[PDB]
Amino acid sequence: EETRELQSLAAAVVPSAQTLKITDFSFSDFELSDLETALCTIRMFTDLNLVQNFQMKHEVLCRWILSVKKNYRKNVAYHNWRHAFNTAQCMFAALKAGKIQNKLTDLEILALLIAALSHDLDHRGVNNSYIQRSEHPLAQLYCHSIMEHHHFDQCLMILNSPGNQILSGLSIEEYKTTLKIIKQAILATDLALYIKRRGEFFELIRKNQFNLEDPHQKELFLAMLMTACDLSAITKPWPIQQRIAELVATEFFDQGDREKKNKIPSMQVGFIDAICLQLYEALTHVSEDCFPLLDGCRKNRQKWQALAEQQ
Ligand SMILES: CCCc1nn(C)c2c(=O)[nH]c(-c3cc(S(N)(=O)=O)sc3OCC)nc12
Ligand SMILES: [Mg+2]
Ligand SMILES: [Zn+2]
């Protein structure tokens, strides 16, 4: 923690969502400094009316954002602060440009944004031996989303740290509801849970039976939305997706957590087909304004496929 970094963040004027470009599905953070990602984050909370509706104190939100950023590991090639930051930006864009904002409640929106930013806290890279070196090396077989539970634990720890309580303004009832949604959302980032609950979601959309007014369906939708934002790097403009794919490959193969290069194109195509396409197609069914995510995904598949055939 840098009181210096906080002082500078808290005293800065937060530029518009327009100037920060956070309403664009094509948004990229390569050009941004950490302070700038912090300012973008404040703007996300502000334009979603969260600061106002939940009486968040400026200095507290600033301190919370810095604490969250500080708890991601920079030595992890992909699952780091920038990835969490980008997931939250996608959530913002889907809520605003994608018009999903009108379909949810303020608490659900509050929970989703916090969850997007916090869902990978303390991530140590896909090739970590966290559980492998614990007193329960078999835990993952009992509780597969055990690491996601740990990410949530980190999130809660920060929300309860002195000077970082951005939810202090909620009533105990609002608070309990928000924490529950935040938990579900973070657990939802366990790709295994996504694969397990996909079918039901695709089925409903398919048979035109999808109804957000149904408490079970709304919860399912929140989980699907979390996945959509968490994988959104796959939807970015070609030059940006190439760079993001480089980071993922690094974490995956060069243990950049704490040959393949020629197989990467086909790998990405397989990933897009097996995991991404269906999800983004389903999302567009719920809200056509989310089409750019689907469009971007398709364009990247075309690009990777061309390379796969080797140019
Ligand atoms: C936790 C990883 C999920 C993920 N997110 N993103 C954005 C990506 C991505 O772009 N690519 C991959 C991915 C998946 C495979 S495979 N064939 O095992 O399903 S290979 C790969 O990245 C290759 C560099 N995986 C991901
Ligand atoms: Mg993760
Ligand atoms: Zn993630």
Image (cartoon, rainbow, N blue to C red):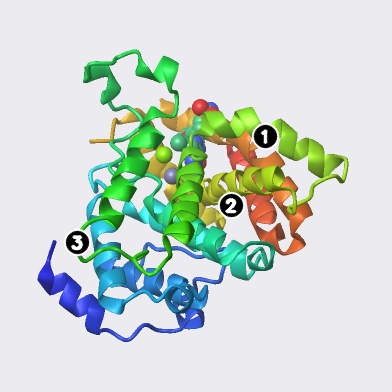
Q: Which of marks 3 and 1 is nearer the N terminus?
A: 3
In this figure, which residue is indicated by the disc labeled 1? 198
Can I make out residue 310 in this image? no
**SS for tag 3?**
loop
Q: Name the residue under label 3.
A: 162
Q: Is residue 139 left or right of residue 145?
A: left
Q: Tell me if mark 2 has few (under 14), some (14-19) or many (20+) residues whose alpha carbon lies within 10 angstroms of its own.
A: many
Task: Give the quarter of the figure containing the N terminus.
Answer: bottom left
Residue 131 placement, left or right of 270? left
From what the image shows, is residue 119 above or below residue 50? above
Q: Where is residue 227 in the image (x, y as percent from the top left)?
A: 56, 44
Depth check: 100 or 39 in front?
100
What type is the residue that disc 1 sits on? Arg
Q: x, y percentage for residue 20? A: 44, 77
Q: Distance between the residues labelled 2 and 3?
A: 38 Å
Could you tell me how far apart the alpha carbons at marks 3 and 1 are, in whole angstroms? 39 Å
Residue 82 occupies which quadrant of the picture?
bottom left
Residue furthest out toward the front? 172
Question: Comparing marks 1 and 2, which lies closer to the viewer?
Answer: 1
Circle 3 Cα neighbour tier, 10 Å, few/some/many (<14 / 14–19 / ≥20): few
Q: Position of residue 229 (x, y in %)?
A: 54, 51
Q: Sequence order check: which comes first, mark 1 or mark 2?
A: 1
Nearest the eye: 172 or 268: 172
* Residue at mark 1 to residue at mark 2: CA–CA distance: 19 Å
Residue receiving disc 2? 235
Q: Residue at x 61, y 70 (%)?
A: 96
The response on whether ligand 1 sits within 8 Å of label 1 is no
